[PDB]
Structure formats: C-alpha cells, structure tokens
Amino acid sequence: STLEAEMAVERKAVEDQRDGELEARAQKLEADLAELEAEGAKADARRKVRDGGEREMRQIRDRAQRELDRLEDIWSTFTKLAPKQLIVDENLYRELVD
C-alpha cells in the first residue's frame, strides 16, 4: 500500500510537470501566434508556426508518453516481480537498483 502510495507520489511528479511542459509550450507558441496575428502576415506562415507547434506538442507529449509507459512499466514489473525472472534491459535494472 505504501509502495503504490509513494508510487502515486512519483506519478505526481510524472503528471504535474508532464502537463506543465505542454501548458508551457502551449502558452508560448499560442502567445507567439497571438503576436503573429498583429501585423499583416500571410496565413500559411502562421500555419507553418502552427505545424511546428504541433511538432512541439506531439513531440514533447510523446517524450512524456515514453516516460509514462516506461515509468509505469517499472511499477508493472514490480507488481510482476518473482524469482527466476530473466531481466535484460540493465537500465530498468538500474531503475530497480536506485
């Protein structure tokens, strides 16, 4: 119970900054699009800032995602921990060491 409790406390460090980065770049590049609509600018250039912004949202969000599935994967292998279980990864193993 304390394992899943402070595991969930670890998931607070997952979810809070996991959302904080996407809100950070979201306010950053959407505010950048807000200043982009000030002058006379071609709309397709703002669509290029939009597409690069989608690369930032999906890219940073997928960096968050591999941390979600890797980090929860640590907890899964802990809940699936038993002897004679052959483990290869050696970094996940360090994630069991620390």
Image: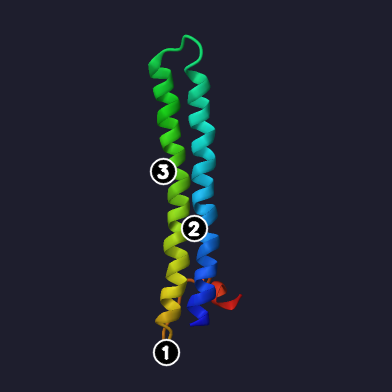
| Residue that numbered label 3 is attached to | 58
Q: Quadrant of residue 58?
A: top left
| Picture disc at residue 15 | 2
Comes first in the chain, label 1 or label 2: 2
Q: Indicate the secondary structure of the residue bearing disc 2.
A: helix
- Position of residue 41 relative to residue 31, above or below, is above
Element type where label 1 sits in the image: loop
In front of the other: label 1 or label 2? Answer: 2
Badge 3 vs badge 1, beta-carbon distance below 8 Å: no
Type of residue at label 2? Answer: Glu
Residue pictured at 52% horizontal, 29% vertical: 31
> Mark 2 or mark 3, which is nearer to you?
2
Residue 59 against residue 75 in the figure, above or below = above
Crowdedness near tag 2: few (<14), some (14–19) or many (≥20) residues, C-alpha within 10 Å:
some
Q: Residue 84, which numbered label?
A: 1
Q: Amino acid at mark 1?
A: Lys
